[PDB]
Image (cartoon, rainbow, N blue to C red; front, side):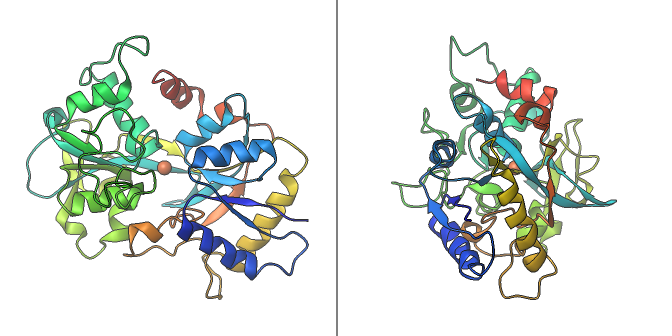
Length: 328
Ligand SMILES: [Fe+3]
């Protein structure tokens, strides 16, 4: 019996084969299918051409719509003060000194993890809109990118389609610079994007600074929704939202057990406590954003199985869910 994972980048593939390689000796075994975009994975998965992929809540949302109707099989666990939780916080990071508040955000540059991802988009944009900041009336008259491209001087937003302003700060080969897996894509990419000065703001996770710049953590602060700017380590108070962990998405069939089995074991032999050269998660550390969050976030510490009961909606929450919807 084999599970076929869908990978979305070469390096992600490798890590994948890696684990398949040192796993081929079990009841359930791996195999890596590499697609172009997560969409194609979602699709293959539904077509029986694959069986799993771990997605950001923004994509989990997507993966749940019809025709797919994929379910969140397992969700990532993250360090909490209280040991652990299945959620993370969305924060907007900023360099220390550059005075400026949430309100003074117009005509700025900004870096985002990618189009429609929780932290780098859904939360921030919808927030900005829910605040009278961004002018958006609706789908049937104006796109969202457009309202976005109208608010910021320019941006980096991997996945962007409708506006070159949004692809303005993306560093890399122009062919692929705004690719969904571009060098400036992902939590860490959006950080570099900030690091490198290509944007005045980064929309990332509460772990973001530590994982790329624990050394120069002092060099950054957080933009709070109230007006303040707090210290990188104050995400709790200075946050824009608390979102659901990324989840592993799979067809609603009988296989969901083979997958959980596979994951349960693998995580057993290669967790944060593994003693192997091979790590399922991370580990976290200043590395090249390109090699980050492969398969799973570098910041995941465990996997917690999801109750069969939950679909995408129940998983995300009626609130977040409506919020995402209302944006498309
Ligand atoms: Fe995320």
